[PDB]
Every structure is written in structure tokens, then in C-alpha cells.
Image: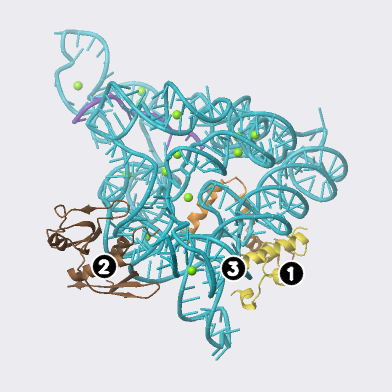
Chain colours: A orange, B brown, C yellow, D purple, E cyan
RNA sequence: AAAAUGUUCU
RNA sequence: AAGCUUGAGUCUCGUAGAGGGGGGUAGAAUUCCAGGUGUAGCGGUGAAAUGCGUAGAGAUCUGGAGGAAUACCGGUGGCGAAGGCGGCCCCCUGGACGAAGACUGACGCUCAGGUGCGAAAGCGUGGGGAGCAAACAGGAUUAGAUACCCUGGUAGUCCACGCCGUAAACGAUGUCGACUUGGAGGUUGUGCCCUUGAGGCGUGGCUUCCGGAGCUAACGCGUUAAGUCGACCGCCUGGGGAGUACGGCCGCAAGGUUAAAACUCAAAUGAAUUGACGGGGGCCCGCACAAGCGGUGGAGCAUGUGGUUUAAUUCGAUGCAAC
């Protein structure tokens, strides 16, 4: 999520933009996922659950 | 594999009856044809049509008396994994003669009663109720 | 809306970076099929192409170097 | 963060 | 004995695929090393400590080494007989599917014994060894804590060639075939159509979800069945004893496999139902908390209780709901 403040632009706005970019990337989430090792089986189960949820 | 044709045919008939199919088609066979004829004679189907030269399709027109099936049940007694041959004395009767046993005999495929009359029995192909 | 299908392509080209880099995000990640609306086969092909590009260093793996 | 158990037969 | 083409195969052209084996390499990241910058913390947790750090850690940049795994794509997506298989590239290689047509002509299906493959762990010899991590150690937590948390950390995880041969190896559903209402998708072909546009109409393969009949103990399953039938094999006969003992066979061992008996219980089990409970979820409430104020528990006395004492200290009330 590389950002650079353009000419005549507030700080807060820039920060917000950066945050948005990060969210889009999925950086924090990714990090969280990689904080601990999930067993492949566990991961698969999770995926399945997600799929089920999606079927509304 | 298609290891019993007669049985398969019977099953098809039964399924048709269940699902309210006006007709039921399958690969024809001489024995199969005979069976169909017998059924027709006895009263359980309307008509059978053996349509084709190289690959003949037997097409049975199923009956539906008062919105339900005429063929109450249709079980193979004889089957490839265990054949059943009855002597004249042994010959079965389906629902105390309110339903037929298609038996293959030395003088053609016929209902059990017919066989009995003749003075013979044989491979009891299928109970039709 | 899948573009590749519309175009009528037999396979996506790794050499065609201009097309590919619409389907990779700013960070360098390969964009999802559900988002871009790509057909599944095409998506796989596209991904492969992207990978190839990265290997050859036409596209970047990530936006760090 | 930490919270163990419940004498028998009715 | 002769045939036939529907089953089963073969060929033509394509198709998608983490199918398998071998070999290359790519980038990110962790670790370590060397060097620079810099300074009191870093690290960790619930909080701590162990640990690492003024010998300069952590942070931060540069260069290197290595090992392992391949973010995103990534999808009840795909392929594989199942196990499983995930960066990209190449070489070898198996299957599946479709399109037509041509050919063989029942060559099929199933299969005890047998043979092969078979996750993970494990074992054997030799390599490798970053990260993770049984064991182990220390620190915590604890009443104890041979655990969960932390810090480390060896075997193992990686590779090569063998062995092991089991898993909730599961869809807890043997294989092959036929048939029976539908819908919503996914995936991958293919024929047709002014593609007048991302479309329209089919027809196949594989596959997820719902759901009809029917089946089921119900749960559910339901054209990929747990429906309807057929072929073949496997397995079951109350629970515990026990998948244990003995023996055999297999294994380097671990063990596996085959598989009892006595004795013993009158249950064991499944599904669902009403409750209750949950250190499950949601909504809501009462001096329930919070917010306050005043107490009690400390003292002296009054009073009741327990206990002890007593000849008797009448009997009863004894968690809130007795005192
Ligand atoms: Mg011929
Ligand atoms: Mg292993
Ligand atoms: Mg540990
Ligand atoms: Mg310890
Ligand atoms: Mg080893
Ligand atoms: Mg087993
Ligand atoms: Mg599963
Ligand atoms: Mg089983
Ligand atoms: Mg269903
Ligand atoms: Mg044993
Ligand atoms: Mg229950
Ligand atoms: Mg209060
Ligand atoms: Mg007192
Ligand atoms: Mg007082
Ligand atoms: Mg008293």
C-alpha cells in the first residue's frame, strides 16, 4: 500500500486513503492469518464454513 | 453391467407406474417381448410395440385405473444370481390368484395358471400383482 | 463482464503487460475473478501469464522493489 | 489470567 | 457353431486440469552471519518472569549464506483409484472429457486368496536442517500443573533409497449397470444461431446446493439416492471383556494383521422430544450491579441460635426460604 501526498492535500485525507488502500490489499488480515499456523485441515474446514455462510 | 434384462424391464415398468408415465421404453428381447405379451393378455398393460430393426425398442403403454397403477407390484422371482424353477405341483400363485406369475415353460412363456392347466411349470420369471 | 471471452482469445499473453496490469492491483497482487468478472479458465490463464511476467520482471511480484 | 469436587439408595 | 452392435474397448482431432516422476529456476518472507547507522530497552503475556540487551540488543539500512514453503490468483474451483496433489519453466509420463466418424465384436461386470498403491506419525542408512516443534529445560499459572500461556529447544518435519501399512484413510454411504418429477447454481467441452451485444436454443462430462415422489428409526437421502431393481464381493449378530489374549503370517522395531475364551452386566446404542443446564448466542428485567447514602462484621449491652454445660437446661424452626 504505497501512498504519496499530492500537491495541496490534507494529511487526514491522505491517511484515510492509505488506510483504504491497506484494506483493499488485505494486509492486516493476511498478517493475522500468518500470526499462527492453521492446519491445512482446519483451513479447509474454515473455507467450507465460509462457503456455507455465503449460501444464504 | 446389464446383468438381467428382464429384471431391468420389470423395474422400468414399476418406475413408470410410480411416476405416472404413459409409456415405458427399453431395449427389446425375445423373452422380454414374450413377457410383455403375457402381461397384455393378463391385463396389466395396454399394448407393447417392438420398434426397430437393428436395435429394436420395446415400448410398453402402461395402464392407470382410477388414477393409480394397475401393476401393484412386479417382482422378479427368478434372477441371474438365483434362478427359481417350479414344478406344476410347486407352481406359485400371486395374491391367491388375484395377480399372476409369469412362468417360462417348455411350451412358451405364460401365466402360472396356464402352465398348471397344461400340466407343466418352469422358470417363474416374475410375480406381477 | 469478461473481456477475454469477448475478444476471442485462445490464450492470454504474458508479454502483453498492458492488459495484465489492469488485472493486477496497485500492490502487485493478482485481482480476483469475482471482482474483475473474468471467466474461470481465462482467470487461471491470466494468473499464469502474470506469474510469467513477474518471473521475467515485466510486472512486479510486490510494490517494494 | 485463575474457578476442583459433591457419600449411597430413593 | 455361426452372427449382430446398443455394452466394453481401439483409432482421428482437439480440450481443461495443484494427475504422477525427474530436473531447473523466481520472488517474498523468517533465521543466521558480516558491516554500517543508532541507544535503552527489546521480547513476551491477562500480567509477569525466564530470555535476549550498554560486550550496543531491538529498530533501521547494506552485502552474503542457507533451508523450507509457495501470498495474491484461490473458487463447496480443478485433477487424481483412494492417499493426495498448489510459485513459474522444461523433459519424461498416466488418466479423464468432448467432436464427429471409422474399426473390433460381449472382449463385459464383480472378485475370496493374491498383487500393487496407501496421509500423518514412526522406523532403517546417508544427506540436509531456515522455520516450526513432540521430548527436554527454565519461567509462569496453579492448591498441585508432569498441561493449557511464555521463553528457549532436540528428534521429527526436508531430500535421497528402503521399510511401516495404519487414520474420523469419511460422503462414517463397496463396485458396475439400468430406470424414476424439478429447480438453482459451479466447472469443463461441443452443435446450432442475423454474436445485429456482454447474449439465445440445445447436447455431453464431472460437481455443490435445495427439494418431489419414494425410502428411513427419525435425522435425513433424494437423478451423483439412503428411491426403484439387477450382478458381484466385503462386513455385521447385545454391551463390556476386546479388536484384547494365545497361536500364525507379516514387520528392523513400533507394532500390524488374523482373531477367541472364560467371566460379567440387562442393558449398550441410534435418532428425535420436553425440560433443565452451559465458564454458548440474542433480546429484556429486579437495589442485581454500577452511582450514592447509611450500616453490619470491631466495642458494650439486648435478643435468638449453635455448641458445651446441666438433674433439666422443654419441644420445634436449621442455605437464600432457620437463628
Ligand atoms: Mg462386422
Ligand atoms: Mg513421513
Ligand atoms: Mg512451546
Ligand atoms: Mg516445566
Ligand atoms: Mg528419517
Ligand atoms: Mg480401519
Ligand atoms: Mg471430508
Ligand atoms: Mg469405515
Ligand atoms: Mg436434499
Ligand atoms: Mg492386535
Ligand atoms: Mg442424542
Ligand atoms: Mg453499589
Ligand atoms: Mg463477635
Ligand atoms: Mg458487634
Ligand atoms: Mg432450642
Horizontally, residue E182 falls left or right of residue B77, namely: right
Which residue lies at the image location 62% right of the left edge and 54% below the top edge? Answer: A30
In the displayed structure, A52 sits above or below E261; it is: below
Horizontally, residue E205 falls left or right of residue A33, namely: left
Horizontally, residue E3 falls left or right of residue B107, namely: right
Dividing the image into four equal quarters, which quarter contains ligand 13?
top left
Q: Quadrant of the C terminus of chain B?
A: bottom left
Question: Disc 1 or 3, which lies upstream in sequence?
Answer: 1
Is label 2 in a helix, a strand or a loop?
helix
Residue B52 has which mark? none
In the displayed structure, B6 sits above or below E164; it is: below
Residue hosting label 3: C35
Residue hosting label 2: B34
Nearer the camera: disc 2 or disc 3: 2
- Front-most of residues E285 and E232: E232
Residue C17 has which mark? 1
Point out residue E105 in the picture as x, y percentages from the top left corner.
47, 62
Is label 3 in a helix, a strand or a loop?
helix
Indicate the quadrant where residue A2 lies. bottom right
- Front-most of residues E231 and E125: E231
Specify whether disc 2 shares its chain with disc 1. no
Amino acid at each position: 500500500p504505497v501512498i504519496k501526498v499530492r500537491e495541496n492535500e490534507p494529511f487526514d485525507v491522505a491517511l484515510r486513503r492509505f488506510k483504504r488502500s491497506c484494506e483493499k490489499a488485505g494486509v492486516l488480515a493476511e498478517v493475522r492469518r500468518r500470526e499462527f499456523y492453521e492446519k491445512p485441515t482446519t483451513e479447509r474446514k474454515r473455507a467450507k464454513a465460509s462457503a456455507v455462510k455465503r449460501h444464504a | 453391467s446389464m446383468q438381467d434384462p428382464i429384471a431391468d424391464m420389470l423395474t422400468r415398468i414399476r418406475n413408470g407406474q410410480a411416476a405416472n408415465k404413459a409409456a415405458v421404453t427399453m431395449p427389446s428381447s425375445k423373452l422380454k417381448v414374450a413377457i410383455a405379451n403375457v402381461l397384455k393378455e393378463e391385463g396389466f398393460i395396454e399394448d407393447f410395440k417392438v420398434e426397430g430393426d437393428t436395435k429394436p425398442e420395446l415400448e410398453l403403454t402402461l395402464k392407470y385405473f382410477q388414477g393409480k397403477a394397475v401393476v401393484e407390484s412386479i417382482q422378479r422371482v427368478s434372477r441371474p444370481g438365483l434362478r427359481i424353477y417350479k414344478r406344476k405341483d410347486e407352481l406359485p400363485k400371486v395374491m391367491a390368484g388375484l395377480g399372476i406369475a409369469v412362468v417360462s415353460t417348455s411350451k412358451g412363456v405364460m401365466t402360472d395358471r396356464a402352465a398348471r392347466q397344461a400340466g407343466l411349470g418352469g422358470e417363474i420369471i416374475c410375480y406381477v400383482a | 463482464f469478461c473481456r477475454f471471452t469477448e475478444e476471442g482469445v485462445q490464450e492470454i499473453d504474458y508479454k502483453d503487460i498492458a492488459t495484465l496490469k489492469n488485472y493486477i492491483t496497485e500492490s502487485g497482487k493478482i485481482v480476483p475473478s469475482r471482482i474483475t468478472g473474468t471467466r474461470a479458465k481465462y482467470q487461471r490463464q491470466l494468473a499464469r501469464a502474470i506469474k510469467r511476467a513477474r518471473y521475467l520482471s515485466l510486472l512486479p511480484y510486490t510494490d517494494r522493489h
